[PDB]
Image (cartoon, rainbow, N blue to C red; front, side):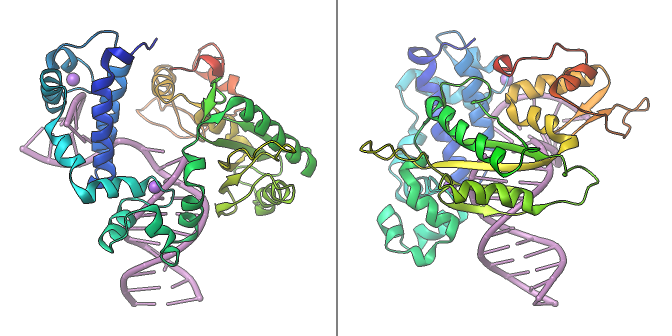
Length: 331
DNA sequence: CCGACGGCGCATCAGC
DNA sequence: GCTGATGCGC
DNA sequence: GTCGG
Ligand code: NA
Ligand code: NA
């Protein structure tokens, strides 16, 4: 259950700025993660907060954050923020990172080499790599929320081609999209083939082939990176005659060994909080999970040998939990 | 006090 | 050349 | 930055 706007947005928002600043400008992921974490739980939090103490209570919340929360309650702002908002470099530094391929080093490098806008980018592509190129290119597309309708749509295309290419494959769209989301950010493609498993001799072709196909059929426009197992690229929906071009979008496809799929599936489907809790119970029944497998916890304190997973269920099976519907994997 | 905090594929870079 | 290390995104 | 050894 989550309410939150006229409630604690002021806070969650400030925090997010904070987080960004750490990541991008700071180069402190942990700190970004920390601020995000705080931002989340408080998001979920049913009350009109009234102080830090109140929030301290939150798990994630703490001293400094709560300190902030007081100024903010009191002032309606965070002074830190104003100097940050007013500091040149920082902002530009935060902006550029928006650009897919551009991280904090690049972004800071650029800003030092004077570059600090799309333009500068545009006027400097000899100074960008591919990934960065496509990202600059697709800048607005990417930040576009994707529509499930489309998702569905997109969902269908990717779905058949694979089917066209080979019949034995398996794919599945994961993410919020799997969780039943009205909208998404990208398309996570989870796939595998029978001929591809754990101790098996890999067919790059497999993945290859699925790409090409989707390529062949002008589904996937660009290509961020690709190798025997992972492919990250740009894809689009064929334009309806006299109907303006939709947006281009993120899509990644992942190939997995059949023995680890569901784990992968399960893993990749989320939620994140869900995974945590699950990791927990699964543990309670004496096992340790991950993206790949499920292991029987050692009678000692830890002990190898992964179990036979033929489904998501099975997973659920081992830990004595009802096979949850991806829909309610909210946690 | 102090370490962990997800890890990994894939591209490009520093080096030998 | 290639190895490993670093950036990036997921 | 927060949590927890
Ligand atoms: Na706390
Ligand atoms: Na970026």
